[PDB]
Image (tube, coloured by chain):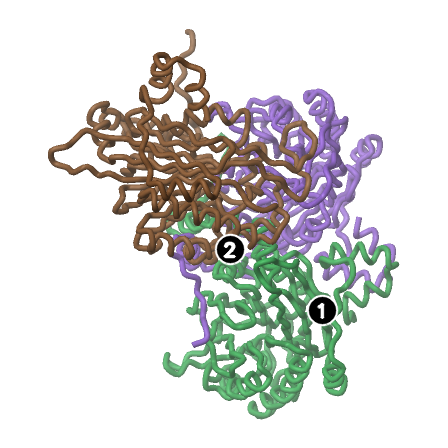
Chain colours: A brown, B purple, C green
Amino acid sequence: NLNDCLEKHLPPDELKEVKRILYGVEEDQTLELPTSAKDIAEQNGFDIKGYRFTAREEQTRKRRIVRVGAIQNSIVIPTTAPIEKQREAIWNKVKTMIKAAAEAGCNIVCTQEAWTMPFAFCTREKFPWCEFAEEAENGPTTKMLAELAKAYNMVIIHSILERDMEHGETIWNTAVVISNSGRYLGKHRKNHIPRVGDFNESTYYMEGNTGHPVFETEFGKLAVNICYGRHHPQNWMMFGLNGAEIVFNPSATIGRLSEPLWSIEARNAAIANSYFTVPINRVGTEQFPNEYTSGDGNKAHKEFGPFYGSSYVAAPDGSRTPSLSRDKDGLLVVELDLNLCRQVKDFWGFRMTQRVPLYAESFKKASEHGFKPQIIKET
Amino acid sequence: NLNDCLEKHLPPDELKEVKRILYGVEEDQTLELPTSAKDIAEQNGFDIKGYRFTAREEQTRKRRIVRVGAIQNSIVIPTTAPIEKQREAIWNKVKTMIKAAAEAGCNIVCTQEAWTMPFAFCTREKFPWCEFAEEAENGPTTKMLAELAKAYNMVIIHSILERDMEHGETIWNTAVVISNSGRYLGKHRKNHIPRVGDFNESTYYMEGNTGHPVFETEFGKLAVNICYGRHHPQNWMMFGLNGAEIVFNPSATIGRLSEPLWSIEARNAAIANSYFTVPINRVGTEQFPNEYTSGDGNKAHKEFGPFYGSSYVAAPDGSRTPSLSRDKDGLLVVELDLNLCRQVKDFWGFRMTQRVPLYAESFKKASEHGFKPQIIKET
Amino acid sequence: ELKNLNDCLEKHLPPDELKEVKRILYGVEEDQTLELPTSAKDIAEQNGFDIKGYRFTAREEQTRKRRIVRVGAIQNSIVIPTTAPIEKQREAIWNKVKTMIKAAAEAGCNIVCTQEAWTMPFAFCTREKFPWCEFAEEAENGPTTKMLAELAKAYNMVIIHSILERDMEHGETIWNTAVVISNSGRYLGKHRKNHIPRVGDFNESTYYMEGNTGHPVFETEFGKLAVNICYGRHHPQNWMMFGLNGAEIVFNPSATIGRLSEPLWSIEARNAAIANSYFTVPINRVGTEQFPNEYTSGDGNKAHKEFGPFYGSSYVAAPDGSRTPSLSRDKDGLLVVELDLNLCRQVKDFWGFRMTQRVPLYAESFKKASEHGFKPQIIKET
C-alpha cells in the first residue's frame, strides 16, 4: 500500500498536507469493524479495511447510510486443471470473503471483472476458456450467489463471462445484479471493448447493447462501469445522467503504463458526476499452459501479470479511500451516506452547468461522415 | 490451379460433366487477349487469363458489355525495410499489372485487401504497421492511382488501411472507388471485423459505419464486400437490395480451414442476389521481424502464410470462372454482359420471393433483449 | 451419364492429388467412413437401394458430454406409373420407404427425413388440379402421418416428412408442409414452405401460397431441428432465421431437375451450414417421372410428358465447412451420418459469425428497403 509507505516516511504535520492533496482528507476516516469479521479475514489470509464517508444533516431527508464491500482476489489453483475445479476453488474463497462482508455489516458486495476465471484473454485461445461462460440468470454462479444474497440480506454485484443461449450462444462480458431478496435484478454488458496488448477481449466478445442501466435497490441507485469503460468519461457521464449514486468499476489491469491511471480515472468520474465510484482490480500473477505474445517486439511467455489490486472508493466531494494491497487478497468495507451526492451537486453545480443539449448536438455532428472539425487557421 | 489438375486427369467426356457440376459450364468460355497484354504479363512474371460471360439479346436494351480486371499479388521486398520502400515496390509491380489490364481492354480494375502492405495484423504490433494507414482521398496511393484511372479511362477499386484525420485519427479498413475520369467517387468501410486466429483485425479497427453503398459508374453499379464480410449472407444481400450488379470481394485468407469455403461463399452470393461476384485473394507467404502466436496451442513463429490466391468471378446464373493460381501473381480479365442480372432475376424469381418485410420483422425481434426463439417442445 | 462424383474422382486421381482435391471440394482429405451393421446393408442390397455411412466429430468438452446423434436421409423415386389410382401410387411409395426406414433403424438412426412431397409424383409441372390435389392430406390426421407415427414409436426415432397438406379448418386450402413426429410417436407440429417457386416446370405457386408458420425449430431429445423446404434453399435469410432460432440441424427436403439447377446443389445448403454454424441436410428426389397428358415448361419448346430427371445427390454439410460425399444421382438411397451436435457451439466460438452478425443493423436496413419510398444507397459521380 502507498498510504502505509507515506505514513512511514513523513512527519505527521507534512503527512497531513500530502494526504489532503492526494486523497481528500487530512487523516483517514477509519471505520471500526466487528472482531468476528477481522477473524475470518485473518484465518483465511486476506486484508480487511473499513473507511467512512459522511454527509451534512438534512431537514427533509434522513441519513441514507449504506455499507459496500469491494472484493479483490486472485485465482486459486493452477490454470492447467479442470475448469470446474478452478471455478469452485475461487467460489469457496470468495464465499468466506462474502461471509466476512456480511458480518462487517455490508449491504452491497461487488466483485472484480470476470472473477470466476483466470484472465485467459491474453492467450487468445477459445478452448477450453470459453467453457467458463455461463448463463447470466441461470448459470451456477448466479444461483449460488443468490442463496448468499437472500441469507445475508445483501445486494450482490458480480462480473462474469456470459453465454447468451437465446442469441446464438454469443459470449459477453456482463455484470449481474442480484437483489437482497435473492431475486435476479438484471444485467449490464460491457460498453467499451479493449484490444490493447494482452487484453485481446475484442477476440472474445463485441460491444454491449444494454445501454447504461442503473439499478434501483433498497440500498441506493447502483451502476456498473465495466473494466475498459474506465477510460471513457462519456460512459461514466451517462450512468450519472441516469441517476446513479454508486458506480462500481470491476476491472483487471496489469502493467507499468496502466497503473498511473488507476488513481486518476475512477477518481475523476466521481468528481465530475457527483456520485460514488468503486474501482476494483484483480490481484496476483497468472501463468498459462501455452506460450503467447503481447503485440510488442518481445519473446513468447506464459506468465500474465502481475495484477496490481489497489481497489479503492472515491467520493463525490473529491475525497477518496486509501487503496487495498497491490498483491494480497482483500475486502474493502466502506460506510457512506448517499445524501452526499445531492449536497455536492447543489454546491458545485456541475449538473446545473453541463449544457447537455449543446454537447448532444456537437457529438452528433462529430459522428457524421462529412464532419469538418472546428478549426481556426491563420488567414 | 484446380482446373488444370482436373483437365490433366479426366477423359474429355467426364471432364465435361464434372466441370458442369463444379463450375456452371461444360467447357471454359475462354476470352482471347491482346498479344501485348500477354507480353507485359510474361516479362513481369504474372499470370493473365481471360474468360467470358454472356447474356440473352434484349429488344429494349443494348448489350451492356463490361471488362473487369482482378489483381491478385504478393508483397515484394522483406517486411523488415522502410515502409515507404515496401509500398513503392508493391506500387511499381501493380502499376504494370494495371497497364496490362488496360491493354487487355478492362474498364474496371480491383485489388485484394490492404494491397499496399504486408498483412501485419497477425503480429498485433502497432509500430510501425499503423504508419501504412493513409488518407482515403488525399493519400499518396489514391493520388497515384487516380492518374492511372484518368490515363487508362478505367474505374479503379482499391482496398487500403484508412486513417481518418477528421475523426480522431482513427484507423479503418476501407475500399476506395476512383472514377474513370480520375475523380474520387467515395469509400466503403469494412462491415464485419474478424477476430479469428492470426486475423486480429479487431485490434486495429472497428466495424464500418458507411452502410452498404453501391457505386453508379458508367461501367455498372459496383459494390465492395470487404474480406470477412464474405461470411455474412446478409451483407451480400444488402448490397443486392441496393441494386448492385458486380460486388467485389477483396480478401486475404490463409489456411487449411478457410480454403474449402473460398469456392462456396462468393459463389452463393452471386446466385442468391443475382449479380456478379469478384472474390480476390492475396498470394504468397510473408514473414515478420518478431515472434507471434496464433491463439492455438502452438509455438511462436515468424512466417504468416501461405495466402492461397485463387481469385475467380461468379456469375448470377450460377456459373463461374476457373480460379487463378494459388501461389503465383495474376491478373484475371473477364468480359461480361451486365444484362444477365435482370434476366436471371426475372427467370429464377429470387427477388420476387424474398419476403423482405417478414425478415426485417423477424430480425428485429431476434435482436431485442427479451427475445424468445420460436421453439416447439414436446408437450 | 455420371452416377457419383466422389466415385468418379477416386477412379482417376492419384492418392496424393485426390487428398488435395477432396480437401478443397469437401472439407476433409479423406472420407470419414462410418461402418454400418450388416443387417442394414442386407435390407439395402435386397431392396436395391444404396446405403452409406459417414461420421462427423467434435472436440471433447469439460462441461458437456458428447451429444452424438444419427440422422438418416431418404432419397427415393416414385414406383408405379402416374396413371394409376392415387391411393395405389402412395401405397407403393409407402411400402418402399417403410423398408428404407427399417434399414435406418437397424443402422441406429435417431432422426429420419424424407425428400419434398415424398408421397406423390411431382405433378406440379402439369398444372392440373385433378386428380393431383387429392394427394393432399391432413397434416396431423392424414393416413401418412398415422402410419409413420407407428414407425416412430416402434423404432424410437424422430421422423420428419414433407407432404401436400389440406387444411380442413382454413377453407380446405392446400399447403406444402413438413411434419415432425416425435420418437414417442406423438405429433410435434408442422412447418409450411416459406418461399414458393414459379419457375419453369415448378408451378408451385399454382397450388399453394407462401407459408404463415414463421421459422419454427423443433426441440427433440436428439437436437433442435428445423426444416427449410425446397425453394427456400435459395434464400440465405431463410436459412439465417432458423439459425437465429437456435437450430442445430436444418433439413432441406427438395425436388429439383435439371442443367441450370444442379451446379447450385453443392453450393447453397453448404453455405447455409457455414454461415449459420449448424448442420445442413439437403435431400433430393431421384428418377424421371412421366405424366398422362402433355405440358409445356415456359421455354419455347414442344409439349412433352417426361418430367426429369431428378438428380438425387443428397448430402450432409457440417458447420465447420466440411461435408459428406453425395448419394447417387439416379439410384434410391439412404444416407446415415453420425454427428456430435457439440460442433455447432465450438465453431460459433472459434469463427465468431454470430458474434459479428450485426442483426440490429440489418433489421433496420431491411426495413427501409421494404418501404415504398425507398431510395437505394447509391453514390454517383459529382
Mark 1: give few (<14), some (14-19) or many (20+) Cα within 10 Å. Answer: many
Mark 2: give few (<14), some (14-19) or many (20+) Cα within 10 Å. Answer: many
For residue A206, above or below residue A352: below
Q: What's the chain of the residue with tag 2?
A: A
Circle 2 SS class: loop
Q: Is residue B165 left or right of residue C110?
A: left
Q: Looking at this rendering, what residue extends furthest in the left direction?
A: A59
Residue A62 is tagged as none
For residue C157, above or below residue A306: below
* Residue drawn at the location 41% of the way across and 55% of the way down: A137
Q: Say whether residue C74 is visible.
A: yes
The answer to which quarter of the image holds residue C158 is bottom right
**Residue C321 coordinates in the image, percent (x, y):** 66, 56
**Residue C183 coordinates in the image, percent (x, y):** 54, 80
Comparing B365 with A252, the one in front is A252
For residue A9, above or below residue A217: above
Q: Is residue B197 left or right of residue B244?
A: right
**Three-letter amino acid code of the residue under disc 2:** Glu
* Residue drawn at the location 73% of the way across and 81% of the way down: C49
From the image, state whether disc 2 or disc 1 is nearer to you: 2
Residue that numbered label 1 is attached to = C54
Q: Are marks 2 and 1 on the same chain?
A: no
Q: Say whether residue B352 is visible.
A: no
Residue that numbered label 2 is attached to = A169
**Residue C268 coordinates in the image, percent (x, y):** 61, 60
